[PDB]
Image 1 (cartoon, protein in one colour):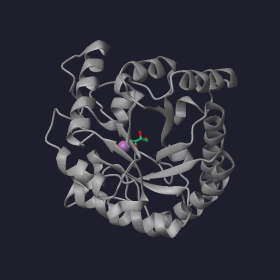
Image 2 (spheres, helix red, strand yellow; image 1 turned 120 degrees about the vertical axis):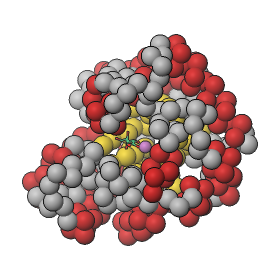
Image 3 (cartoon, rainbow, N blue to C red; image 1 turned 45 degrees about the vertical axis):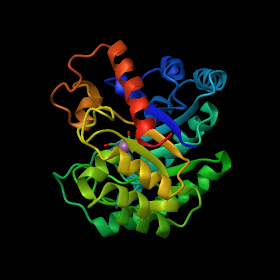
Image 4 (cartoon, protein in one colour; image 1 turned 135 degrees about the vertical axis):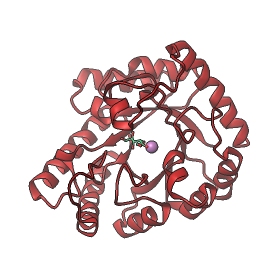
Length: 290
Ligand SMILES: O=C(CO)[C@@H](O)[C@H](O)[C@H](O)CO
Ligand SMILES: [Co+2]
C-alpha cells in the first residue's frame, strides 16, 4: 500500500535547517516519510547524520531527499568544469545520504533549478550532457542502493522535461534501473492535458509523486482532481511514495525559489499548519480509497 510523506520546507523559510524536529513531527502526524533538503545534509557533521538516521529508525520514519542543483553545479552545462563540479557535489550529497540512511533523491538532480531565462540555452546540448551526467551518478548511486527521481517541472522552472512524455523519453534513454520519473501535481496541472492520464502514461516509470493544490496549498484547499488522481494510482498499481509538498509561506530562500510573493497561510502558526496537514492527509487518504 502507499506510503505518505511531507517535505519539511512546509514549515521553513530556508533549505539548510536541522531536520530532527521534523522526524518527531511526522511521526506525531502519522506520516510514513519525511523528505529533507539535500542542501541540509551535504555539509552536516557525521555525528548529526548518524543521529538523524538513528532518530528515523527509532520512530520507524523513512527519510527521502529533495534537491534543486544551483547553477554552479549544473550537470547539464556545456561548461565541462561546471558539469564536473556538479557531479562532484551530487556524489558528496549521496555520501551524506548513505550516512543518514537515505535511499531516494529527487528533484532537479539532472540540470539546475530554478532556471534563469535571462541568458541563452541549448536544449538539445543540455539534454545530451544531462543524460551522460545522470548515467554517471546512477552508477555511483548503486554502492548505496540509491534511486534518482527525475522530476517533471513546469516551463517556468526548467526547459528540459516539462511533461510526462518528455520525462518518460528521457528516463528510457538514460536506461538505468535506479533512475525513475517523479511527477508533481503542481507541475502536471500546468503542462499536462489531463493529470490522471499523465500518471497512467508514466506507469512503471513512476518512482515518486509530489502532491499539492494548484497554488501549492495543502490538498483539500483547492480544486485538484484528487479522486481521478487516486484512480490513476490504482490503475498503475502504485504502492510507492506520495509526498505532500505544500508551500504557503512568503520570505526566505524558500519563498524566493518557489516565487511566492503573498502569504497563502492566513498567517498560520506552526500548530495550525500541523492541524491543516493532518486534516489534508485524512482527506487525501479518503480520496485515494485507503
Ligand atoms: O516541485 C518542486 C519545485 O517546484 C520541488 O519538488 C523541488 O523540485 C524539490 O524540492 C527539489 O528542489
Ligand atoms: Co515537486
